[PDB]
């Protein structure tokens, strides 16, 4: 079932679709903030206040952070992962930024067992490529300011290091210049939609993760548009790809599969390789509708399917290399024999070029070192991960 290929050609099908829209209810927003404040004055939540530097009204936002395991509890005031609340210049309480609900990998929670999924969800199933960077949230404030956030933060960090949020905003400025639109226009459009744009910042020249994003592929991969309400309502992916084209984002590849057993089959087939349609793929985020009643009312619901290998091995090599440099014992947990060889190769590379240690610590040279060892071994990552 690898007839299915991730596509960024869906924007055309969006012509027949219409964006979900729900306005905010200030009373429900106030009640949510009250419940979050109470929680914070003791399911533990942390509040951080940020000034919006660009705001002509001196707007401030409160970022709310939960522990990822607390999302498994019932009766949370919200399941948003990334949530920023504000008061307008008029004293109205609003959600400024709303992330996706926390979602889990297969067999991580009762809800994400294949039996549970098969029973309680309905398709069509959107399989969205899981791009490997940091999350960026974009929204428009009541006063017209474009807000750009990382998962829990906004603004530049006090030193000469660029924050993730500022780096995201600099990519956004470039993509807007390219298509001839402004931050003001984007802020007005997101406010009109009562929406948060959800993107993955992927740029090796800024920070390396595991998958490579060279200059031609670097920027903001738009993977979501959420409504700024306590509930979770997200755009269908073809409308996300249409918004991506209109506002100069990179598109997130999409596969729509009707039948849940075909979804399972496809994902298991890719799991063998950890690659799809020529490219390395770290995972998929599967988007569908779920009902509490297994046969009631339906709500937008996500789960992920991570591909364990070779990406687990690569992450181990990165952490082992940073330990080597820092003097802490490398934690070898898997791929023991090939990792022993990698660490001797790494030690040789660091001895030959002593600049590399400081670069590796700043998340530059990590992918190159991994690929240099694999070339040295005349192996593909997938082969290296299969040895053990
Ligand atoms: N198509 C997509 N749909 C949804 N999320 C996507 C995505 N592509 C990438 N992502 C990223 O996947 C993240 C969710 O993954 P999770 O498994 O919940 C935590 P993670 O990916 O291990 O990273 P984190 O703990 O550093 O946030 C989102 O925060 C977003 O940054
Ligand atoms: Cl309205
Ligand atoms: Cl992140
Ligand atoms: Cl308004």
Image (cartoon, rainbow, N blue to C red):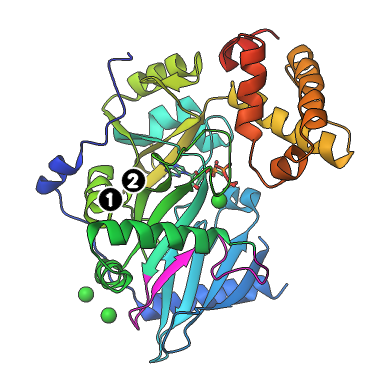
Mark 2: few, some, or many residues within 10 Å (few <14, many ≥20)?
many
Q: Which mark is residue 149?
A: none
Residue 193 rendering spot, x and y as whole percentages: 26, 66
Q: In the rendered view, tell whether residue 320 sits above or below residue 268.
A: below
Q: Quadrant of the C terminus?
A: top right
Does residue 229 appear anywhere in the picture? no
Task: State the image quarter where residue 1 is shown.
Answer: top left
Residue 345, magenta (yes or no)? no
Between residues 134 and 96, which one lies in front from this camera angle?
A: 134
Between residues 168 and 375, which one lies in front from this camera angle?
A: 375
Q: In the rendered view, tell whether residue 379 sits above or below residue 28.
A: above
Q: Is disc 2 in contact with disc 1, using a CB cutoff of under 8 Å? A: yes
Residue 134 rendering spot, x and y as whole percentages: 53, 49
The outermost residue toward the bottom is 90
Residue 171 rendering spot, x and y as whole percentages: 42, 56
Q: Residue at x 42, y 72 (%)?
A: 95
Q: Which residue is mark 2?
A: 250
Left/right of residue 33 with respect to residue 55 in the rendered view: right
Q: Residue at x 28, y 69 (%)?
A: 182
N-term mark: 2 or 1:
1
Q: Residue at x 46, y 17 (%)?
A: 268
Q: Which residue is mark 1?
A: 244
Residue 157, magenta (yes or no)? yes
Q: In the rendered view, tell whether residue 385 sits above or below residue 119.
A: above
Residue 334 rendering spot, x and y as whole percentages: 74, 20
Left/right of residue 214 with respect to residue 371 in the rendered view: left
Q: SS of the residue at dot 1?
A: helix
| Magenta segment boundaries in residue numbering | 140-160
Q: Quadrant for ligand 4?
A: bottom left
Q: Residue at x 29, y 51 (%)?
A: 235
Task: State the image quarter where residue 258 is shown.
Answer: top left
């Amino acid at each position: 079932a690898s007839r299915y290929k991730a596509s960024t050609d869906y924007a055309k099908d969006a012509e027949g679709l219409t964006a979900p829209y729900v306005s905010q209810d200030p009373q429900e927003t106030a009640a949510l903030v009250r419940a979050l404040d109470d929680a914070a004055k003791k399911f533990s939540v942390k509040k951080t206040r940020y000034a919006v530097a660009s705001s002509p009204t001196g707007a401030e936002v409160d970022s709310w952070r939960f522990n990822d395991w607390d999302y498994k509890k019932p009766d949370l005031p919200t399941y948003a992962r990334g949530l920023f609340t504000t008061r307008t210049q008029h004293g109205v309480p609003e959600i400024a930024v709303r992330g996706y609900d926390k979602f889990f990998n297969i067999d991580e929670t009762r809800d994400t067992a294949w039996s549970a999924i098969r029973e309680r969800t309905k398709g069509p199933y959107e399989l969205t490529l899981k791009e490997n960077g940091c999350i960026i949230f974009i929204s428009g404030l009541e006063d017209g300011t474009l807000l750009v956030c990382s998962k829990h933060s906004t603004g530049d960090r006090s030193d000469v290091a660029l924050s993730h949020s500022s780096a995201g905003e600099k990519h956004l400025e470039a993509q807007l210049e390219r298509i001839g639109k402004t931050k003001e226009e984007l802020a007005r459009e997101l406010r009109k939609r009562n929406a948060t744009a959800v993107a993955e910042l992927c740029d090796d020249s800024f920070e390396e993760h595991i998958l490579a994003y060279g200059p031609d592929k670097a920027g903001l991969y738009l993977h979501g548009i959420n409504l700024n309400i306590p509930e979770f309502i997200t755009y269908p992916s073809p409308l996300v790809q249409k918004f991506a084209e209109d506002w100069g984002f990179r598109k997130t590849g999409l596969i729509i599969i009707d039948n849940i057993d075909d979804v399972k089959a496809f994902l298991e087939e890719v799991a063998e390789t950890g690659a799809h349609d020529g490219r390395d793929v770290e995972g998929f985020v599967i988007r569908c509708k779920k009902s509490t009643n297994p046969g009631g009312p339906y709500h937008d619901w996500f789960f992920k399917y991570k591909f364990e290998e070779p990406y687990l091995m690569y992450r181990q090599w990165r952490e082992c290399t940073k330990a080597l440099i820092s003097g802490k014992q490398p934690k070898i947990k898997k791929h023991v024999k090939i990792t022993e060889e990698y660490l001797l190769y790494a030690r040789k590379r660091l001895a030959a070029d002593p600049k590399l240690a400081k670069l590796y610590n700043q998340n530059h040279g990590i992918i190159k070192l991994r690929n240099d060892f694999l070339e040295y071994k005349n192996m593909k990552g997938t082969d290296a991960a299969n040895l053990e």
